[PDB]
Image (cartoon, rainbow over all chains, first blue to last red):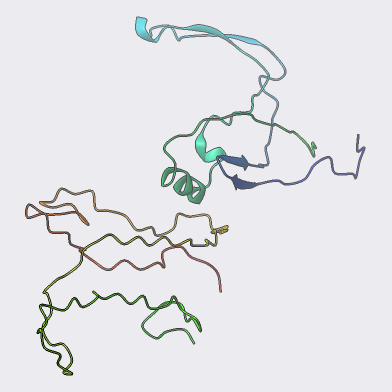
Amino acid sequence: ADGVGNSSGNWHCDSTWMGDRVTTTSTRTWALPTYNNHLYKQISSQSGASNDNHYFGYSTPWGYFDFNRFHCHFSPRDWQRLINNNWGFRPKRLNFKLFNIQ
Amino acid sequence: PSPLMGGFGLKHPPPQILIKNTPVPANPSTTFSAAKFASFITQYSTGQVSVEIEWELQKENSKRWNPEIQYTSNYNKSINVDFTVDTNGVYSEPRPIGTRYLTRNL
């Protein structure tokens, strides 16, 4: 889309309060290494662990983007503005973007 | 011309509203007297007064990161709640509250 030398996005970190809505936007810089050396590895609890700590699963070479915390979208001033003036809130919709990939 | 005691300086402020009871003369003499009336029926008046003011607000548009100072009630227990009536039903204002809690850059 933008080959080499053309930016594919802009930095949008801000919040807009409009009546009964607040739209919070956040931008961060991420680093993604190579996980498991491009391999899927079966993982399980160590031998000798207690029965409560036993588990079985798989480790993937993929990563994931997590923003399931309020601090990822609300500044402390935004939080104070939200909690001192509103009797409730709920999420409505979200937009996600990855850009400027090197 | 901002008032030194605080507030808004107005060249044409809200007008003074003057109210008084109309004097009702008491029993006059059956003979004419040119002296002005000095005896009146004692009376007072009671009623209701309504004042409605529309205020314009300048919304805060700050971009500071950390939280601001806000006026708040104190959570700790107390014998009386602030800005309420006591067991005598007497309303009191425990402290003066200003308006300068949010912050703006110079």
